[PDB]
Length: 34
Image (cartoon, rainbow, N blue to C red):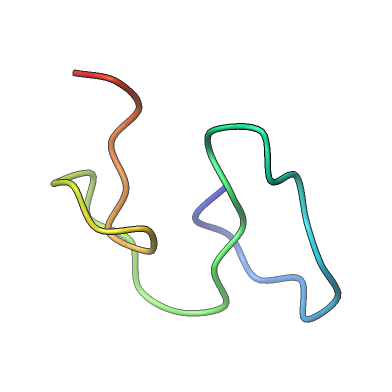
């Protein structure tokens, strides 16, 4: 997840957003259950 794809990526828990990730909470700024 957090890396670009365009097409639907792994929707399990850590999905692949096509923008900037951070690991904070948001679905693109994504932190797995922390």
